[PDB]
Length: 108
Image (tube, rainbow, N blue to C red; front, top):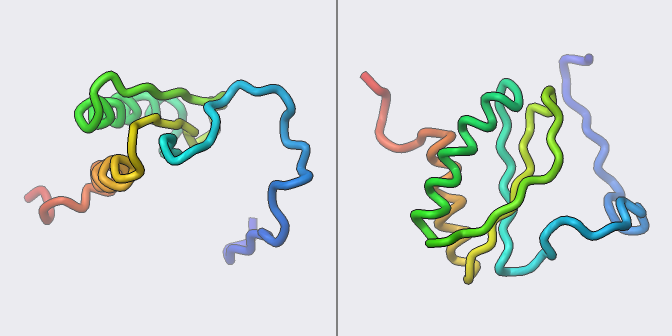
C-alpha cells in the first residue's frame, strides 16, 4: 500500500507453465490485443459495447473473444482478428482516443 510504485518485472513468461489447455486465439499478425480498465466489470461491459462498434466499422464481420474476467478485475482482456497489422494501429488509435477522448478540446 506504499504511495510510491515499485513493480518487479525482471523475468516474465517462458517456462512459466502458465496454462496448458488451448482456448484463446493463436497469437499472430492477424490478431490484436485490447486492454481496457474502469470502475469494474459493469462499466467495462458498457464501454466494451462501444469498442465493438469501432471494430465492425473498421472491419466488417470482425471476430473477437474475451478471456475470463472477475467482477473486481478492473481490467478486461479481449482480442480482435482483422486481416493486416495496419488495422490494429488504426483500430487501436481510435479505440484509445475514444476512451482517452483526446479528440477536440474540452466539452464546454
